[PDB]
Image 1 (cartoon, rainbow, N blue to C red):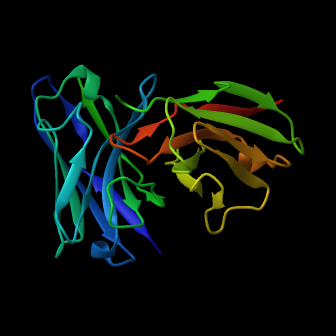
Image 2: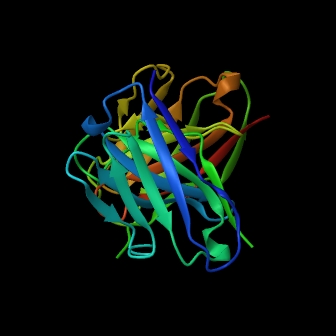
Length: 228
């Protein structure tokens, strides 16, 4: 029973500081990495940084490095994200997400529920189409393009409305455990695709791709797959 619980969000004024907390339970905290990814409309998913709890080492997205600080408390099984000099641009849902390895250049196997924060040389991942209407029992293929070669270091996530993302595929074509057989991914280099061989009602969602070849970790803008 993997559980990630974020807390500490709220409504703040420009220039404020805010500390977020992520409580991990149901697994050994020090065996996995801990990242912070934020999401807002029109801004998509944006990697903040991650930390390897046994080493206490962290990597950041250059756009927030020095302003935001990640830390951990191994005895508490908790990762933290310290926000500073907050601006209108930092308005987002802040997720903590687990990385299944000892590298900060990775994909995430579990995401928390998110905590809302409101203030009042990069590999570009592009997804197309932005939206696609489809009907049940149909085969659908969606695309993801990397601005430069990423070998097979690509992950696909599904996000249903009101929910956090869920891992579908990692390593471009490896299906995540418990994911239905109707999902497949293919590609290498810069050209990637996700296919659902026969749509089920649960498959109507937004799909994101993410590269984990270089820093910063970057996400595509998403494809919303909707009924008829």
